[PDB]
Image (cartoon, coloured by chain):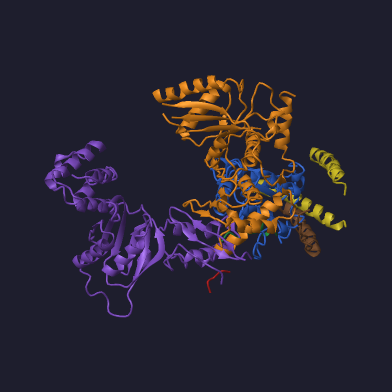
Amino acid sequence: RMTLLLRLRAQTKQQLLEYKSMVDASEEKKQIEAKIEDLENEIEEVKVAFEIKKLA
Amino acid sequence: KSFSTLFLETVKR
Amino acid sequence: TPLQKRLESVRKQSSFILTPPRRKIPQCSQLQEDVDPQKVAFLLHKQWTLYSLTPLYKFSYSNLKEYSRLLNAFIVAEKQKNIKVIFSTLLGMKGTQRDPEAFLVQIVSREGKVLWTGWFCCVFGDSLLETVSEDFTCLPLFLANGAESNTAIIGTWFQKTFDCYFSPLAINAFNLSWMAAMWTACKMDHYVATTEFLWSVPCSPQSLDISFAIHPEDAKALWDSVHKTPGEVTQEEVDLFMDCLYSHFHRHFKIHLSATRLVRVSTSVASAHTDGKIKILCHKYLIGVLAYLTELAIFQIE
Amino acid sequence: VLRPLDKLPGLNTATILLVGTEDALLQQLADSMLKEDCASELKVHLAKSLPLPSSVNRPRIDLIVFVVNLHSKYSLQNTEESLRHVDASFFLGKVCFLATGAGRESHCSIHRHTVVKLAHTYQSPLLYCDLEVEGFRATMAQRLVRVLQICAGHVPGVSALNLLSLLR
Amino acid sequence: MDETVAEFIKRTILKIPMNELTTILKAWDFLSENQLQTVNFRQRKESVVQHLIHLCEEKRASISDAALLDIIYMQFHQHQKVWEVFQMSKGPGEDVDLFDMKQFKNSFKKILQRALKNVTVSFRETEENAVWIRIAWGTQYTKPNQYKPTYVVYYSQTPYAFTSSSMLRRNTPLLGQALTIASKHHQIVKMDLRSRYLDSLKAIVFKQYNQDSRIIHENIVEKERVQRITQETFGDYPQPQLEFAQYKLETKFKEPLRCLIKFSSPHLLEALKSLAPAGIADAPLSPLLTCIPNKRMNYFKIRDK
Amino acid sequence: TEEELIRECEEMWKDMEECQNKLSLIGTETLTDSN
Amino acid sequence: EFIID
């Protein structure tokens, strides 16, 4: 069971992660050549924000 | 808490 | 340039960058230069089974007699495993002056009972000429009509002597709908045949086929309903013509024709199948129908 | 109108909802997607069009794969019609565009660019396969089920939001 | 043992396949039980088609029974030579109290040779009570042509008389005329039912054919409905029309917009039945397409209404 | 063990129940046509 | 009618 409750903790620490991300995106209220550029500079910066997080 | 399985498995029915 | 140009072409083709080819309505192609009226007229109302033909290595339009003998001695030897083979340059089945002249391969049996009448043509195929070297005389289209057995023998001879390979050209229902739309957009008179679209539903146990044959003048007036920009037909205009067919068929029989696939689109210009036995050439638009067919053969080769 | 987070998740339940006009092929894909005994509950949903008649108790749907049968233009006109009833917050990670019938390339009433343009203009992964054959189904089923655990959050490092950053 | 008879028998004996050689050669009665053992039916095609025709050379075969051989060949190969359906209609009065097969054979041959003086009409009263007329045509200027005959399956006392749609010449209005005057009717009408499966046309014109826990299908309330509506329009065991069920549409697109729809399937009414459940068709599948047997019609000529 | 783990696990359940009631009050279900 | 819908 503990392994199953562990798979749950993990799954919920990510489902609430998604929930908080979406509600923060809903809390907030252009250059498509750079719209993917200020899309890329997070997918590298969230990447350094969570590869260090996973690494910790 | 957690209707989930910790209820459903325990209340298997 | 000699190969890397073709590699860049392959890159462009595989990229699939906004394809919708707004195509010019097939313009009345006044028969260029010679175009032997007897030969071409014999070549029109014959059901050509299309193939995709890779460029022929070390081919020359001077040694037609030598290839004729070399292939005649090979065909009758495949009977050992009565027939004459007449390679005949067509002199006019070409879109631009730089295209290779189309040439025939006829299995003439006593009298002129042309059993097979092969046909290699490269018209408006300058997406292949500018990428292949000089040694190859590229004719992307190959046209059978003779039995499949003789085609699968002359194709082997051509592979053996010229390093050209015949993939059976299969026009997908998308390209089929395209050509079914640009042929009812033509400016012809005295429509020879009704505009028939042979659908074939994808039922697993059964194989019901539909012949949505429209009156050819009635389909021209239906095309004018969805035709707004002249000179060039768009993908949206083709799709709206096809969807007006869909909304006149599902309206009547409550079966969604768009859920089926085209298998044959007969038109007053040129009939066109899917499985290969495709191009009947009723009218003398064949330099435009063949232009589309060669452009489709490039897609398979390149 | 379907929303990604309208319902609460279960525990290991990864609820994918197939979308395609043809339904025997959807049933085959669902059978292959449950053939492997994976580590996740896999309440696969089928459909034909995204209005999805309004029945409450439908679980938190974690994936919508729009099975676009390239052989039939209906499967696109019934996907593009059904693409307008998906929440804009649903199109981020939890949307895939299966293109069955691709590769046969002789029955394709739809040019595979058109499905490429559709799956690029909606910013979502597009996974070609040929659902009619189990050899290409029993490997696409294990691709939809590992995308499933990504969007449903079962792999504890990658969100559905992180997913499309990988399949761009 | 004659011109256009011996070689005609040869051409109808290589037509019949090797398996049913005994079946057709036993029924046409020229080869008695003793004659069957003389020829080894299992050896070769050209061997049997040469020894059997010799067995009629000694039997002095005539076209009257050579045509009966063709009849018996088609009785097991009726699934070729697509069949038109003629529908007779008596006016007000009692039925045909005298359909004597002898009298009908007389009243048909007499009327047919009245105008088509050179025809070889050969009847075969089948055991399903349906005279299987075969007509080899030819005008007075020519000999009767057995190359392309016009078999007419007239059910004995039925107003419906099937017809092999061979060429649809000037004899077709005489084929119907002789048919409706031999059997004591007055009006012959082509039903416009034209199918290759006579065993299904017989069914149609006589109305004789119907007498996982994980996979949550969200559109189950719609799949159940479409399965329901495809079971109250196509009840059970549909008959194979297998015919070009034309719909010569003349309707305006929503002056007219001419169309010539031709549904073409090896088994049509079953192909339509598996359409709506397969997602190709809507659940109420357009009675134009469901009422092919209900209207006893497939060669439609619809208009707008 | 599970007593302590389901403590915040169901507390995370309460947080999704609020953030969902937060997401059930925005309720835009905004559509996306072409473009 | 002649159910042309």
The residue lying furthest to the left in this view is E34
Q: How many marks?
A: 0
Colour red belongs to chain:
G
The residue lying furthest to the bottom in this view is E93
Viewer-proximal residue, E258 or F22? E258
Colour brown belongs to chain:
F
| Colour for chain A in the figure | yellow
List x then y, in percent, for residue B6: 65, 56
List x then y, in percent, for residue C28: 67, 44
Colour purple belongs to chain:
E
Colour orange belongs to chain:
C
Height in image: E89 above or below A53? below
Q: Is residue A22 left or right of residue D80?
A: right
Q: Is residue D78 visible?
A: no
| Colour for chain B in the figure | green
Q: Is residue C219 visible?
A: yes
